[PDB]
Image 1: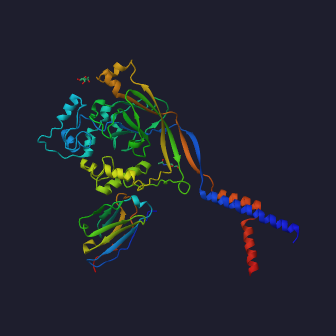
Image 2 (image 1 turned 45 degrees about the vertical axis):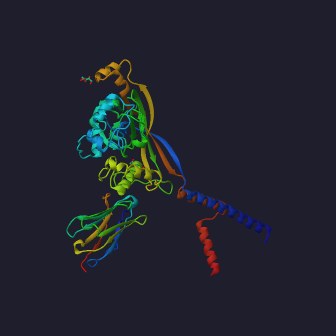
Length: 424
Length: 116
Ligand SMILES: *[C@@H]1O[C@H](CO)[C@@H](O)[C@H](O)[C@H]1NC(C)=O
Ligand SMILES: *[C@H]1O[C@H](CO)[C@@H](O)[C@H](O)[C@H]1NC(C)=O
């Protein structure tokens, strides 16, 4: 037991402390399951054009609501009082109030059956009326190109939905005149009159748009942006494909051939929420709002103050953790940039107000032009990458085990052999 | 993968009570309506009962009304059919599958025969 032996043994038992204090650090670091992001910009010569849902901020027209419609659902759509009578009409236009009062007689009126879905599909705004000239990549478009969808805003329309077997439309050039370009007439004179401000009374005009991939359904109620009449609105989109990491690295639901949804063929963070709401309503009181899928009968207007708004508020506010919507491990989303130009120029005001027989004032306050296009033909890709894999773990453990004590797993096996041979 | 195995069903005496259990794997049943079916020997599957994903709503057939009970156990992947007052008219193999999410492998099914 000399000083060389003692010093060497002490240095070994000192170098063995650092080895463990570092190996356990690496093992813990691996078991945190860290990741890092990789952003890239892939240039492409073709991008599939997104689906463009949009619809008027007016749920449904005033010239289409009828005597029958005003009876069953007059109270719901905020035109009649509780006792089937018109509320205070101090701030009421004379002609508008007379054209409503004759619709609210109910003198020996024999009500007919009422279907809320049928009401929306009839009183809602018609694309054949709003759409004045659609264009796509300079080729004339049509009102038959817009598919009818039903949302909380009523009867909305989706362009390039990719549903009903139609092929999704590709775009070949960026820039302004190489995408969708629709002139709309929001029909501001069909808007429901506002006598008194209720909780939900809305004073705005214009339409609401959402730009989404064809996989997910429209969700304009939360994901839309407004565009205003009398304004060329350029919407420069940017495709953005996102790869996420499943557990344990992240929290995402790897896409399977089928969806984990009772009402939707494919899975989406939005389809999940719509499915949750529909299932909750159907299981609670056996009816669905007009905008939900499935087969249950639509709620009658009586079942909206007794079954729809209460249950939906209950689910949203305090009961919010029934359905946890895992967000898919990859999806394409569309960023956007908005800009505006005045419509119409003094040069072409009269041409429009003659092309449509309407007044120049009307054209000024009713006509808008969406112009949705890709800025440049490339897509951003945002990936989550696993930051420390098992091969890296073995490398980092071996390279320092062989730096501090110069051992290997075979050296440990030989040491176990020797320890066994002693004990025998 | 989607197992959806069904167990706990055996031949029973007429006017007897039996309990049928299914173990759905492969999907989050928490958000899946679950239905029971009768494969009549030589005939197509006929729905027996359906329960909502939340368990609040129960649907039955014509002959199943007020004779069967459907129970759904959450976080246990088990659907319970509380059969009662059985008759030979319901002697068939029983299949449990998601009602609205029909594109799934159908399990073997437990045969219950109400003879004696
Ligand atoms: C999901 O990501 C994969 C690549 O990771 C891709 O091939 C697939 O198209 C993506 N799914 C959808 C619905 O975009
Ligand atoms: C336009 O002017 C008024 C608008 O209501 C109408 O009487 C007339 O028929 C319209 N003419 C055309 C050609 O649209």
